[PDB]
Image 1 (cartoon, rainbow, N blue to C red):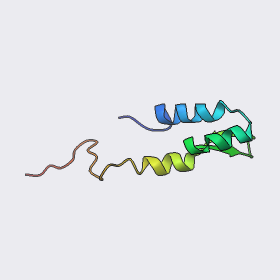
Image 2: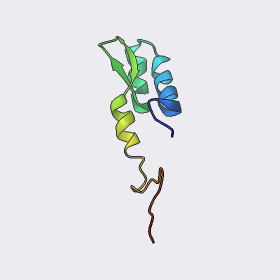
Image 3: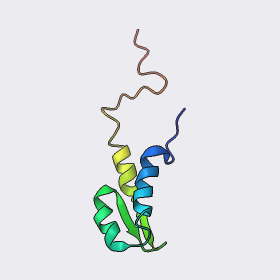
Image 4: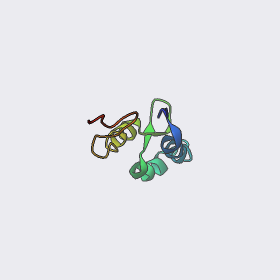
Length: 73
């Protein structure tokens, strides 16, 4: 199956953040896009916080059939 360790969503997100490199103000502007300045590494990094919290928001209802939705009868 398809695992989500980054994929497209996190790639472009991270890339937008990394496009600011280590400019804090630029990252502050990109904050709306999921970019958070990380002082630890000293760069604009993807907010994995929001990335995950948004991902678990993307469960639609709950019935995501990955192998089977329901056997029913």
